Every structure is written in structure tokens, then in C-alpha cells.
Length: 431
DNA sequence: ATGATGACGCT
DNA sequence: AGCGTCAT
Ligand SMILES: Nc1ncnc2c1ncn2[C@H]1C[C@H](O)[C@@H](COP(=O)(O)NP(=O)(O)OP(=O)(O)O)O1
Ligand SMILES: [Mg+2]
Ligand SMILES: [Mg+2]
Image 1: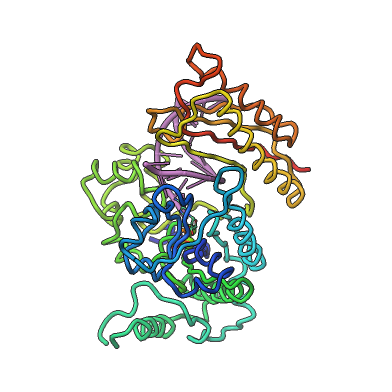
Image 2: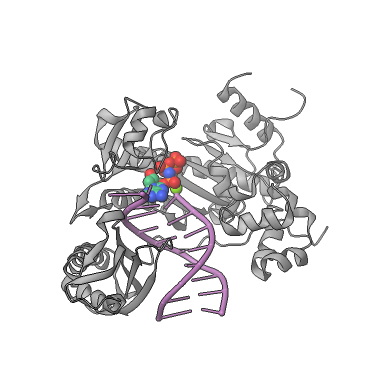
């Protein structure tokens, strides 16, 4: 009781852009705004693969991974924006540059951990402490939380529209707050939410992009919270909200449990919801899923997690990849060499920009391929030295380290045909 | 015939 | 090192 940790020591937010690549294209092309629209990659195979979808289009059932020709059957008026293609492949530069716009604004408020092209975790523990002193015991107005939901509220003995509900919950939360105790975790979360309102206002003002956010005591809860009221809203998940929230929360919805581990938790334990994990001892969970995973599950199902927000705003690897599906699999040596060069050229461009912007150099080159028949993401990875940002040298070196995979006796050919090439620059050092 | 990426764990 | 998992 007195010595039980409650995982309420930090304030962590997760900020995730709403239909990010779509907003990037809508900002650029006003004709796309407030329309069902999607971002597509490679127009020739069935209109292109959809990689992002506006909320207007989601209402028709359009999803990521859908072929655009198929999406158009669901949504005949769907508008599309195409990803740029350079050197025969998708070029995501526009979206990486937009991401930097957003990450640079977030970084003004606090230390961030870049988690994807469109989201970052924020450790607000310090900013909250300082804001609480300046707020010398002074209450927090609902006007300071105009887009905040309080998960689990309203509740109890007590409107039929969304915003009425939001407000009722926020009112219940604020009315019950203990503002004279600067160490109240619920107060710390609330002030955290005020800061995230400010952050999200800054992003929208300075970029035009809308986003959602979660505010809680750790990364897994903040990420889960972010998604509860997307788009263009933020959600506070308190420690106290966890038992009800988790009581019907499918295990696969929790970060890192969406794959085989989560499926094994479900099968082995015979459970469906996160909250059901509380029934097991830490030793029991470790017995089934290993020391690290077992400890992690034991704490997480109680709303407790210690994974820190890492101070990292920049990616640790820079890579370029291309698939060659079906009949397009590379079958000749000259083919393989041409495409390695295309990849190397793009990688060179990105590395050179990276070294100028960020004062660092990559020192290792990883070359990965996939062969026909293999369902694995990669069939084979080999590394070599990256000593010069030169595309012809990188492409030549990549060929050298993989050319032995050519099981064939031919000279002119390549077998088995290659269904993927991947060049990744790694192991950065200061420069 | 999703694709193009990116982080991190395991042995 | 090279492979596998999980992720957007
Ligand atoms: N499997 C994938 N393959 C290629 N690009 C992808 C991708 N998943 C996402 N992207 C690209 C395209 C996405 O725009 C961007 C962010 O991904 P999200 O945050 O998962 N989804 P969004 O921001 O679109 O919508 P909302 O967050 O409101 O649900 O990353
Ligand atoms: Mg997003
Ligand atoms: Mg995201």
C-alpha cells in the first residue's frame, strides 16, 4: 500500500498528426481541402496503393493499403494526390520536410522522442512543475482545455451531442481537482494537457496541420489515449481511468502487443482484454513470456510502464528501399546494378543533406535483399564500410557484398530473381 | 502486387 | 554480425 508504486511519476504526451500525408497535400493544393481524398503511391498498378486517407474518405470505408481503383468503388468522388517519384521510385522528401516542421515546433516546448514520420512523445514532467509554480495555487479554467477529453468522464448520477459530452466530463474532472497539492498526479496531468493544448495550437498556427494527442503517465497510455478521440482532439488518461479503460480493451491495441506476442498472451492465458492480465502473478507472466516481457506486462496491465522518452529528434538510420513484385523481379546482373545505383543516388542525396543539417556522418552501409518465394521482410542482410558519400561507390560496394547470392552459373543473369533491394546508412558519428 | 521506411530485441 | 518482431 504505502510502498506500492503507481507509475504516476511522469507526465508524457504523444502527439500524432491527423491524416498526415493528406494534410501535407491539402495544404499545398487548396482544391483538396475538406474533401474525401487520399495519397497514393505508383499510379500504374490499379490506380496506386493508398498510404493515407482523409477523414471524409474514411467515412466511405477507404483505408490504407487499398488500391485506388478499389477505393474509387467505395468513394466515386475520391480525390487523389500522388507521391513524387524520382529515379524510378517513391520519393517521400515532401513528407519528411513537413515532419521536420512539426518536430521543430514541438521541440520548443520540451524534449521529444521522434517515434514516426508523424508522431513524437513529449516528456512534460519538468514543464508541468514550472507551470504549477507560476500557477501559484490558481485554479484551472475549462477555457484552457478547449479540445480536451477526459477519458472515463462524464460518469455517475447526472446532452446528446459530442461536444456537450466532452464539456460535461471536463467539468466533472476540473470540479474534483485538488489544485492546492502541487504533487497531485491528476493535477500534473491537467497542467500537462494545458501545455499540449498550447503545443497543438502552435503546430496548427505555424504549419496549418491539425493533430491529436494523448496525455498520461507513460508512453503506452499516451499513445492509446491519442487515438481515443482523433481527429483534432486530445485525450487525458489518468491513472484512475485505467481499470475501466482496460476492462474492455483488446490486448492487441496496446503498443508492442499487436503481433505474435499479443496473440500468444491471448492464446496461452485464454484472455481477451488487457485488464484480465492483473489476475496473474509476475512470476507466472515471466514464466510464459520471459523475464522482460513478463515484468513489462505485469506493470502495464496496471497502467504502469517505465520506458523513458528518449532525447532523440532525428532518425538513427537513413535508408532507401524498393520492391520488385511478381513478374518485375530483377533477373539480370545489369538490372540489379542499375537499381542499386538508383537507390544509392537517393541515399547519397539524403546523407549529404543530413551531414549539412545535422553535423554527422554515417559509417556503415547495410545491404538487404529479398528473393522470390520468401515471405520474410528481408531474406539476407550484409554490411560493409561507408567511407564516402558517393553513389557509384556505395552501389558498387553493395553489389560486391551480395553478388555471391547469385546461386546461378550464368554471367549475364541473376537467380533467384530479386523481389527487394534495400540500402541503409547506419552507425552515425559526429562531424 | 501494398510500399517505403524506421527502432530495437535475440543469440 | 545477421535475423526477427513490431511499428507507422
Ligand atoms: N504502412 C504505411 N506505409 C507507408 N506509409 C505509411 C504507412 N502507415 C502510415 N504511413 C504514412 C502515411 C501517414 O499519413 C503517416 C502517418 O501515419 P499514421 O499516423 O499511422 N496515420 P495518419 O496520420 O495518416 O492518420 P491518423 O493518424 O489521423 O489516423 O505515415
Ligand atoms: Mg497520424
Ligand atoms: Mg502516426
